[PDB]
Image: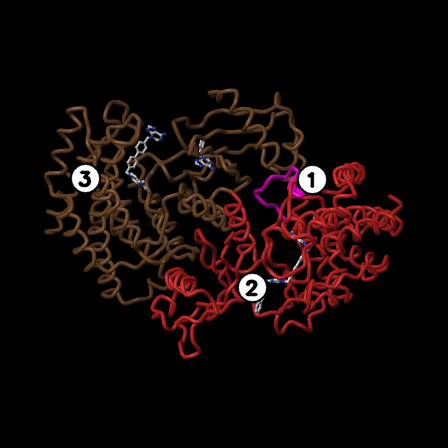
Chain colours: A brown, B red
Amino acid sequence: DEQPEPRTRRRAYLWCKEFLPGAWRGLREDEFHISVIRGGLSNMLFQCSLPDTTATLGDEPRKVLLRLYGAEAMVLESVMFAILAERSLGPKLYGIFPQGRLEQFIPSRRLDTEELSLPDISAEIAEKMATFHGMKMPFNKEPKWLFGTMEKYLKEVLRIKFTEESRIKKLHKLLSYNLPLELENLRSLLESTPSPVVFCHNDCQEGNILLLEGRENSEKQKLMLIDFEYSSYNYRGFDIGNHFCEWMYDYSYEKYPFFRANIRKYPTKKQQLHFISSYLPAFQNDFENLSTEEKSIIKEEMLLEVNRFALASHFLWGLWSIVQAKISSIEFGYMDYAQARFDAYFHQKRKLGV
Amino acid sequence: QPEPRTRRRAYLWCKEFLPGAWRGLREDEFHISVIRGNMLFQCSLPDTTATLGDEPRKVLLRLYGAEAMVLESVMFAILAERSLGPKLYGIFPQGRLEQFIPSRRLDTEELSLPDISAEIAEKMATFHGMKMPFNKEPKWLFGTMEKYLKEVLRIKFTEESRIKKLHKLLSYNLPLELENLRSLLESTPSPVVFCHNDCQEGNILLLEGRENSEKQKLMLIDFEYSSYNYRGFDIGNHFCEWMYDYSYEKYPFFRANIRKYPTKKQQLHFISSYLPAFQNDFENLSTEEKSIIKEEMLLEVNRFALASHFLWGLWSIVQAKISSIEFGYMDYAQARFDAYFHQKRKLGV
Ligand SMILES: CN(C)c1cc[n+](Cc2ccc(-c3ccc(Cn4cnc(N)c5ncnc4-5)cc3)cc2)cc1
Ligand SMILES: CN(C)c1cc[n+](Cc2ccc(-c3ccc(Cn4cnc(N)c5ncnc4-5)cc3)cc2)cc1
Ligand SMILES: Nc1nc[n+](Cc2ccccc2)c2[nH]cnc12
Ligand SMILES: Nc1nc[n+](Cc2ccccc2)c2[nH]cnc12
């Protein structure tokens, strides 16, 4: 129930008063209710609401989420959020302004990492993912995001110099793998791994999945995927592979390095099959009406596909994490997260026999 | 034809943003011609190229040229999603790809046809009712008039005849006049609504093959100046456009005709169509109550029309300095002010 600093309170009041219709337009500053949802140095969240004793005038919301950035991609993220809201595939957009936005408040909690493996959950994550992999979005259709971003991080990574000895020591270990050659070896493997270019979330982890309040007894319609800011047209294998990788990481751990990694929490073949059996009919529409041997061939190939791209999830977020150790001031063990992603990378390679 | 650099940029945008036969277009294959310009262009496959299906054969490319883009972009995307504007096919830093709508623009003379007018009023009402994630304080109208007035007072032209016209315009005492206008409009109730702000014939498409529809043959396009504004401004502004023909083939490249302003009857025809499309419980009011609403509405829009003359008059002065396009802006500015003083005389205000 934490209060923002009184200058933020005033700015939030004005945005709510001017952007929101109905009882909000005539609210005084002293009637305004706000509490921090999440702090941090950027992308801060607040809940704003009317007094309980204030009646609504029409269909205006009683309660909204304020998102403050704390600063091209700005236009792309804004248009995407607007489109998704229009398609009921995300929170409504109530206000956009240079410092942030006002969004629909969705009563909910995020999933915990252990919940990702629950069959009803997985099935539904697979369906939602298939669904927006299917949609049209006014963005560049060339799949350059994946390797373009890896190349960009690699370049930054090679330029990095740390001063603190345990960071320099850890950086020496990661560099000793020859990351540029590893990149090329990975590129070449993925060039021979067919994967359809689709519109990808790119960050489908539990923290970005909402368990809808009141819908816990719905078997197949209780979730919403959020936080599409890293979306792009990309290889389907990445979006799915990346999601499977996230089974292994728990970001709620309270001691340094502030995550737990468990190589044994990666989904089993049966768990993967259950995920892709739910994905496939939702994305192909009459997939169930194929011969069993053809369904099977598609499924076995898609498993190879997402498991090879899972390797790009490790390599890419490994590199990202090294970069974060340099530029971020967040309390998170970035170097240790990097080493965990590379460990998983080579363990995955050995498993696949590549 | 366009600049060979613009041709190249445009070719890559179509190739990378659009599905099907666009994805493997070779380069010598790209058809593109200029259509306006904030430049517009038509991009197409050659006739020879068959579609892989579902992808447009023709598209419009828009370049912004000389944050506003964020708002305009979100806005266009919303209208496309709602089926109110052209579809959005690509969005990028310098501009966008849009659906090409087989259509032509209306001519000035067509604004006054009863069916056209009735439908313009209905589309406007519908545009007005919609919710948009933008600032709802109606600060647009006078904020923009202030900003242009300030620039106009600093403006200096090099050429003598422009200096001479600016001097006549400045002698009306525009700062005092702005305050009289403000005070008149602060006492004229007008609901705040999502306004188009530029509802003229150049921005209204007559849809191809739909010419026989009495009530559904048009789309309002080009909403880049949109904002929450007083409803009276959009309407009065639209009325003032009955006076101006922008297809005049010689200098100053417009005809102004004060007698073409809608008559009371034509105004009533427009608002009788607007009201039931904006309120919807309006059709069920008593006859006398409708009559009261309409007569107040005539005063309302006619008074706001003064702000259309005043604002675009000032705007036109600034454009004279910066726009190298061919249009006599100083003469248009004078035409708007003549109209402003005539309308004040007509109103007793
Ligand atoms: C799409 N991108 C840029 C990705 C980057 C990294 N990954 C791997 C990954 C995922 C989550 C996390 C992570 C770390 C900490 C948290 C917890 N947390 C969440 N919010 C905050 N403000 C936090 N401040 C400190 N810790 C905060 C949540 C997620 C770290 C790395 C996936 C995608
Ligand atoms: C909402 N805003 C910014 C407005 C500004 C001015 N007005 C009044 C007005 C409207 C149209 C025009 C105008 C002028 C010329 C044209 C013709 N035209 C049309 N397209 C071009 N590329 C032209 N190049 C030269 N002339 C061109 C069309 C409309 C001038 C003033 C209304 C709204
Ligand atoms: N638009 C949103 N609505 C709800 N949540 C989740 C949320 C629930 C309870 C408390 C705090 C946050 C979001 N998390 C991110 N966006 C939203
Ligand atoms: N999206 C559009 N589709 C069609 N027109 C009108 C148009 C037709 C033929 C040639 C030139 C313009 C527009 N004018 C502005 N936008 C459009």
Q: CA distance from mark 2 to mark 3?
A: 48 Å
Instruction: Depth check: give the residue in front, B221 or B193.
Output: B221
Amino acid type at circle 1 is Phe
Which residue sits at x=22%, y=47%? A312
Q: Residue A267, which numbered label? A: none
Q: Quadrant of ligand 4?
A: bottom right
Instruction: Depth check: give the residue in front, A106 or B255.
Output: B255
Q: Quick check: is the Cβ at mark 2 less than 8 Å away from ligand 2?
A: yes
Reading the image, the residue beneath label 3 is A158
Amino acid type at circle 3 is Leu
Reading the image, the residue beneath label 1 is B142
Whether residue B331 appears in magenta in the rendering, the answer is: no
B209 with respect to B170 (left or right): left
Query: Which element carries disc 3, helix, strand or loop?
Result: helix
Which residue sits at x=52%, y=38%? A97
Rendered view: A201 above or below B15: above
Reading the image, the residue beneath label 2 is B36
Q: Which residues are magenta?
A: B130-153
Q: Quadrant of the C terminus of chain B?
A: top right
A345 with respect to B230 (left or right): left
